[PDB]
Amino acid sequence: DMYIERAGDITWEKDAEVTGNSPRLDVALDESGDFSLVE
Amino acid sequence: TTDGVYRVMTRLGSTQVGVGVMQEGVFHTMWHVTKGAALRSGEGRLDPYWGDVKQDLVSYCGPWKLDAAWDGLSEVQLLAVPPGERAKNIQTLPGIFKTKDGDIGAVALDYPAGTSGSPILDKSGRVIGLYGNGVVISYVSAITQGKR
Image: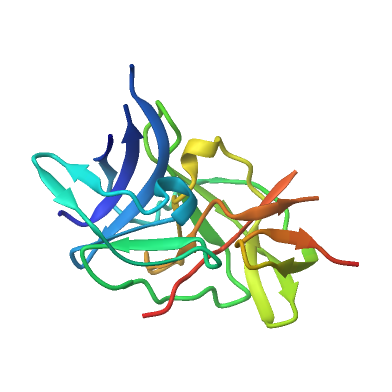
């Protein structure tokens, strides 16, 4: 069985770690909700 | 029922299958996390109210409440709730999924699968979408938002 447990407030944190790129990707979304790359 | 971010757990032992957002009395997560199953919250039960496989979203106890959207320019924060770790904020500039139907923000962050449903926040603290439906190029998640 599936259950939920509170883990925190929804808040922005001023001291957050910062990481990751910002790629621009062409994609398609199919009926099953799956994204795939397009060329 | 308290507003906040929550782990979605299953049971021999317990495993974290995802995350979701309680806001305005409604629980929001990704369809692939729960497959629409009812959820326990203490002694109470949360039943699904709306869901859509193509958007990969589901709401419990009422209609989808989250409506903010990425502004297309600003950094955002993934409020990641990884299995076995405290909730933590990861700031990033989204990239973009370009589709035939318009552009969707995307975050190039690769967290454990049990992190799916974690909210992505704008600078005001509003939830602009949920993490965990995406593509591999590294994994890149759409910023998936529903309709209020």
